[PDB]
Length: 134
Image 1 (cartoon, helix red, strand yellow):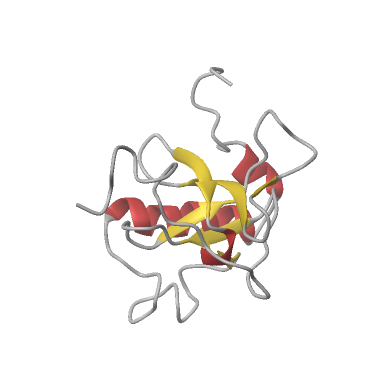
Image 2 (cartoon, rainbow, N blue to C red):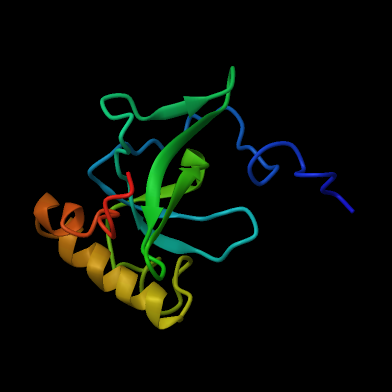
């Protein structure tokens, strides 16, 4: 029963101090999350824009969205974000590390690939532009 009440804050688990993996808004990033599978994502700037970090002392989190269903967004472990490349790359192709075949994960590789391999207009066109509920 390793979750008393709410287990700390958001999903209990924090990263640590990085010297690896630092991607800020406008880019494609592949993110992995704490109890979830591997996910091809977009790093996006939320209505607190011009600054992009959430931090507690000597540990950092950034805002991104994940190309899931609606899609989803939250504050992620930035050290679990990988850079903008796609479906033809050895870690994004079959036998690759981020490659889970769910049609949402493959489509997210194709949608993330079309935007990252071309222009910003393709990724920010989707962003997390579902309904203007801010």
